[PDB]
Image (cartoon, coloured by chain):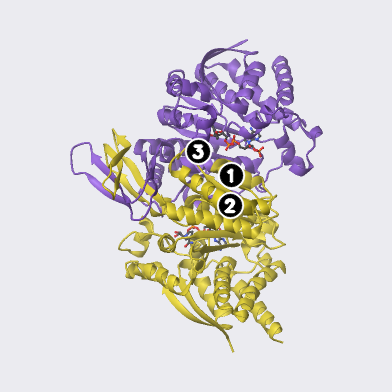
Chain colours: A yellow, B purple
Amino acid sequence: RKIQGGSVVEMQGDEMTRIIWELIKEKLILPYVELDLHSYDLGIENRDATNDQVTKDAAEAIKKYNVGVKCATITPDEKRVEEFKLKQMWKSPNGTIRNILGGTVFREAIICKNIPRLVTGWVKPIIIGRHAYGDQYRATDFVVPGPGKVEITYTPKDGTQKVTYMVHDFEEGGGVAMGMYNQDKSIEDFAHSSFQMALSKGWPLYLSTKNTILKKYDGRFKDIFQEIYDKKYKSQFEAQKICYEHRLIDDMVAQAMKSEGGFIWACKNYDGDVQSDSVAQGYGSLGMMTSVLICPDGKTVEAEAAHGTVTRHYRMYQKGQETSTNPIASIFAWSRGLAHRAKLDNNTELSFFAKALEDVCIETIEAGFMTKDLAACIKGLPNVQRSDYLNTFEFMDKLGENLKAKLAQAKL
Amino acid sequence: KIQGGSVVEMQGDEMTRIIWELIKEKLILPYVELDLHSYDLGIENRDATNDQVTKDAAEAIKKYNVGVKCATITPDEKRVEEFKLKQMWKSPNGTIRNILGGTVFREAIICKNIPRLVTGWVKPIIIGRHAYGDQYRATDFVVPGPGKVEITYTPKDGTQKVTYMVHDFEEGGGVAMGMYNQDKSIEDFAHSSFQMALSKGWPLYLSTKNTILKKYDGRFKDIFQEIYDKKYKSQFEAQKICYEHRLIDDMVAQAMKSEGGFIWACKNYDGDVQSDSVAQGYGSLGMMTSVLICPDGKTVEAEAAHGTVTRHYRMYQKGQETSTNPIASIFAWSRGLAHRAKLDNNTELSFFAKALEDVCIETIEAGFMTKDLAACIKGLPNVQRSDYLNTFEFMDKLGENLKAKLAQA
Ligand SMILES: NC(=O)c1ccc[n+]([C@@H]2O[C@H](COP(=O)([O-])OP(=O)(O)OC[C@H]3O[C@@H](n4cnc5c(N)ncnc54)[C@H](OP(=O)(O)O)[C@@H]3O)[C@@H](O)[C@H]2O)c1
Ligand SMILES: NC(=O)c1ccc[n+]([C@@H]2O[C@H](COP(=O)([O-])OP(=O)(O)OC[C@H]3O[C@@H](n4cnc5c(N)ncnc54)[C@H](OP(=O)(O)O)[C@@H]3O)[C@@H](O)[C@H]2O)c1
């Protein structure tokens, strides 16, 4: 009989990842695990259909059952509005889910011994702790239509002084403007998650900001981290002989590039987004990275691929060009989500299944069966033959065969 | 000595200040006579003049069209205490760029014997960094407690004011900020980017986060596309190159895995961050050029992209030997003087500028380099003192080779 897995919130997505997502459920999950699957279609059409209510409903469900596994989703701009005949330019479902749940998105490469990196020195893992709240991802932006002043105003609840700051006086023509923000409590949760992750790994921690330029905004991050360190984690850090350091983002990305890895990197929301993809590509592929939102309650997680819907491959798929999209990141959303589900329930069999799922992925790749992106890592793109890799369906089938075999052995 | 002409010089801070004088003393003035308009943008003098020296320097560049700037300290609270400053002064770079406008073009300085950290970059990556607006001319503040932050637009013509909610802080405080950009600046940004692509013969990529900042970043995307479809597309096809917008996180990955050989138009912030990422990728922050090209097509400001290298300066203060790479600071002068030459049809200064650059590359390729470059070759753990020269040892070697090169031609 199948493993009794419990309640998991599933969020279906878009385009190429939507296709892969179904193959994963059919070939790797459902045959072995029976889940109370709370499914929410976060495909762009359904979101438009529900006026994005389905996205909010999914986030609330994650609060209830403590485990979310999410497929990559289209975040629409004008072109997407035209493409799907949308009612509105809906906000990022990820931004909405993260805004509701809070926490830190931890991202890390998935490493195979036979895959060369683009960055020579990274023999140890780099873990990015991405602050999941605020800044650009909950901003209020608009087009400035012509000459006029933009100002930003603070009005305290407590009737004290109201303050108006000049943003810019557009003397001729227009442009754009935006306001963005963050909250002390969220920054504090972010700091705590960062120090704790470093202590659990036994690695140094770095925070990057641009506090020289955003003296107040980014200065707040810097101050809160330092304060929380001096009060809560300093002695613990000293005991494990690791350090915490603040660096300017400029300096930090250069430092990361030349390091050997083996550190925790606390990033502001935007930096965490951009640099996690830089790092993932650095180790080999966007297809080879885990991403898990760890919420402040220490119980709730949302696992996801860090990459998008892989539109370009999807276009190929729509035109019958054979595709070779890497499913590993999407598979690890399931394994990481199921592993947490297992941990909460002390579900030994589910834990075993989740690790076995990950082992199958690594073993299969290390045995020389891989998608084109990984084959490109080994051979270099110009040297890649069709014989060097498997197409998307072939690779999924190969994983399914290897998983079946591995789970069959273990039972014997 | 060569008669250079009028150049605006800006002195800086810490390690780069030292190097800056070494450069002038050995590599420039011994060969070039300059109408040198010097401004001390050191932290001490900026404080002394209430940062007026920085604005004066900017106006000077506009007048004489050539500026060469040394790296400067941008003060935060720690700098305020360290130097007992009157105020937390704004970045002199931000101030200068805000006045001059333009695009900061950044690119690695390549030596054949220096291994990269990124295996695939056999061709160069040129970043065009929009030098105006966004985070670098923003208004930020601490939110002291519960309350609402709103952003408002008041039309100049007296029509209806518009107010947007930024955030209602219901519990505790936080931070907030407003930032902006201008259509004309974005347009100049676009033009400078397409033109650079065409002059280099390479494809052009613009990165934004327009899926998230739909209005703000969408404007950048729309302005680039419009200008492309109307002035540069035909030329692009004719050179068999192309323009493409990408989301920033896609772009950084694409860049990481590419062979190089493209122009990368970045918003101010991305240009800042990714230029350091790329410089380090090719080998060293010390090995990158940075040139602000102003929208008038005649004014230029050259600089090092890296900072004042405070950590090396700290060792220097404690008497320890330092090995800081001067090449970027040297190229600030060479790029500045080279532009000065093009302006004045000065064929003898153009030669000197090129000669200064060739001497740097020749010397490094001959096995004489600072510790950072030696670490590229051997690996940091395997570097020994015999593998490199200290800052002053290296500057002297450059001094000799320069003179010989000039003599021979
Ligand atoms: N977490 C999320 O829900 C999320 C995150 C990012 C983007 N998105 C959305 O996804 C859509 C497409 O965005 P995008 O094209 O900028 O980024 P993307 O979907 O991540 O893909 C961009 C490029 O990255 C490479 N790539 C990403 N995942 C890959 C994989 N699994 N296997 C092999 N290669 C992979 C491919 O490179 P090559 O083309 O060179 O082969 C692909 O064309 C957009 O609508 C965006 O809003 C969603
Ligand atoms: N253009 C500018 O005026 C500008 C730009 C950036 C920063 N800054 C200012 O500079 C100060 C220090 O900033 P920061 O320490 O974050 O950055 P930084 O001075 O650029 O460099 C920090 C690290 O980068 C490496 N590095 C940079 N330039 C180098 C060179 N020429 N040769 C060898 N190594 C080099 C060193 O690495 P290792 O320690 O590993 O040896 C150094 O410790 C700050 O006050 C900042 O405001 C100014």
Figure quadrant of the C terminus of chain B: top right
> Looking at this rendering, what residue extends furthest in the left direction?
B159
User: Can you tell which mark lies on residue A265?
Assistant: 2
| Residue B362 in picture, x, y percent from top left | 72, 28
Residue, disc 1: A252
User: Can you tell which mark lies on residue A57?
Assistant: none
Q: Which of A66/B209 is in front?
A: A66
Mark 1 secondary-structure assignment = helix
Mark 3 secondary-structure assignment = strand
Do tag 2 and tag 3 residues touch (Cβ < 8 Å)? no
Q: Which amino acid type is marked by label 1? A: Met
Do tag 2 and tag 1 residues touch (Cβ < 8 Å)? yes
Q: Which amino acid type is marked by label 3? A: Gly
Is residue A118 visible in this depiction of the protein?
no
Query: Looking at the image, is A245 positioned above or below residue B356?
Result: below
Quarter where residue B157 is shown:
top left
Q: Nearer the viewer, mark 3 or mark 1?
A: 1
Q: Chain of mark 2?
A: A
Mark 2 secondary-structure assignment = strand
